[PDB]
Length: 9
Ligand SMILES: [Ag+]
Ligand SMILES: [Ag+]
Ligand SMILES: [Ag+]
Image (tube, rainbow, N blue to C red; front, side, top):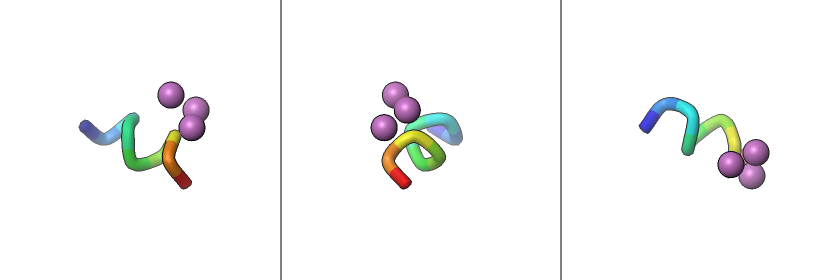
């Protein structure tokens, strides 16, 4: 989940 946030942004 954390990585998905960083990736998205
Ligand atoms: Ag991305
Ligand atoms: Ag990415
Ligand atoms: Ag990604």
